[PDB]
Amino acid sequence: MNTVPFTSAPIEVTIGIDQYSFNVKENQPFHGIKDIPIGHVHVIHFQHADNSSMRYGYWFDCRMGNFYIQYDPKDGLYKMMEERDGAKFENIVHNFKERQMMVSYPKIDEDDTWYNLTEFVQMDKIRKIVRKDENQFSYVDSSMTTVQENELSDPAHSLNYTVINFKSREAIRPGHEMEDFLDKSYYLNTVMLQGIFKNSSNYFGELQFAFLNAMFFGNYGSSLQWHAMIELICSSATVPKHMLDKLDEILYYQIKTLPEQYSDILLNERVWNICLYSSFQKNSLHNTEKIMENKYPELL
Amino acid sequence: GAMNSSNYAELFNNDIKLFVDDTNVYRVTVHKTFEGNVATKAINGCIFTLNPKTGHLFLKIIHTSVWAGQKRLSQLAKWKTAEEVSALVRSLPKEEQPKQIIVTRKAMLDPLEVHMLDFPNIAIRPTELRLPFSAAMSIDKLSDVVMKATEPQMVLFNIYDDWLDRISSYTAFSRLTLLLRALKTNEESAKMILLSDPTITIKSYHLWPSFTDEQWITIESQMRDLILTEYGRKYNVNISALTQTEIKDIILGQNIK
Ligand SMILES: CC(C)c1noc(=O)[nH]1
Image (cartoon, rainbow over all chains, first blue to last red; front, side):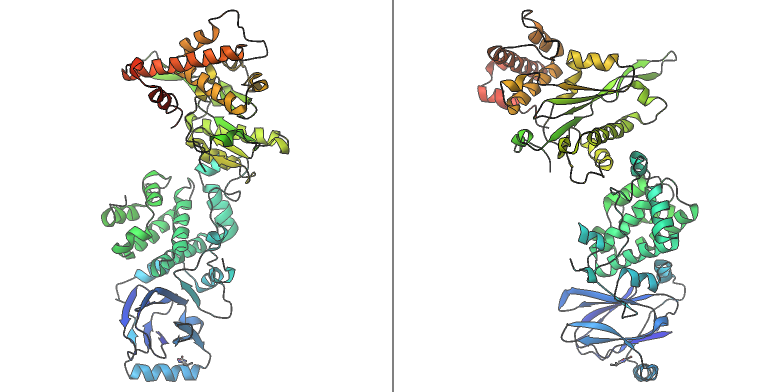
């Protein structure tokens, strides 16, 4: 079970670790997070107490290095860093653990929530969406725009989600205009799955990452990408049964985890109504349909 | 954005533009079957593609064979319209291609946008104008070429005849919309107004009669009288009692959506 120490907590902040969160007071003797489950990506995230516009975090995998958090008083944020000296890192973690200055990743044994939300998410695909090749971890924040949003402006600080655009030459074969616009199967199966993603696992990984960035950072472009990737499948008459069954599980756990209070900002009425009640796949998402109708019947 | 009352003069500037009206593309008669069910029978239709500055009308005749063995015809009709407008644009030399295509019905926007992806600089716009282009098939020579067609055909017309020799495009378009609105409202009364003086004929090469400038003023009056008479009949309104600005705001509230 891996550990992310913190040098200190000089400013009052809400710290998220995956779906959990806790409040740290200004100069509280907080020195990090232990017992982080090996075998999944994780996200550590921040929202400053004195400025809720500061909302940002780091995707990481403790299998790829020894990572810690240090506050930078010049740039005014908590930065992830990699410790290259294994012996120093072990000694720092040991001292803090002995002094009980770390919170424990509060995983209930029966609880697969985080696996369910990150099943297809891999750190190597994250590092291609978020381009900073000198670090093994990835910074995301609430204001980062997508390559798509930038087209419709700093290219280095952008989320390189796969561009999906239903009224584009990529989506529509000349000669098959009506066919391809009303049935997105060509665009999903040939262009996106066979061509760009190579397989459904990569497509679902990007969909899951987009949702998590929308939920944890309120990242608007991420929310757009998440909905576009659901709509592209729901709007396709021809989708492998395994992919529909898997999508129903993916969406069920995303809707289950979404805070009730953020449902008005995180859920697009048009896409969800279209996907559940009008689309080719309106009868293929039984679990997602049931949780949506029981949790968010006002949206529908 | 949307073409409305505010931006009407834009229709008569030197930027090539076309109106596309798809009302008459898919046309049916509805009848009882032997078993007492209901069936449709398609009849020949047309796409009404008009340059409002020049009067050039590209009348694509939609022959009933287009529909044979096809499903969801009202949906397909929009996409067939978009396919044919995009084929017409590709057929025109570059200097004749429109800068803008204004669709009379908002349901034509996505079909036309998708067919015109290869022309990202041609703007596809809706309009707030209520235009009576559905009444094209009340023009005897247009109805005749559509119904006689035995195969898909494009026929070119100037819907203003020679009017632009004497009047501006603004005035010609105003005259056309008034005539079509009158034909839409009461076809038989409108035709009787146009055809009643046997000494004024339609030239072989024209759609409308050969009225002098003074006769066009009389005809226009008679058409505005027909439209107001029919509004009174429809709403049970005493027209004789209305003021001149009441009358203005009915005749030209009917050509906004
Ligand atoms: C670099 C130093 C401040 C450090 N703190 O925790 C670490 O793993 N390294």
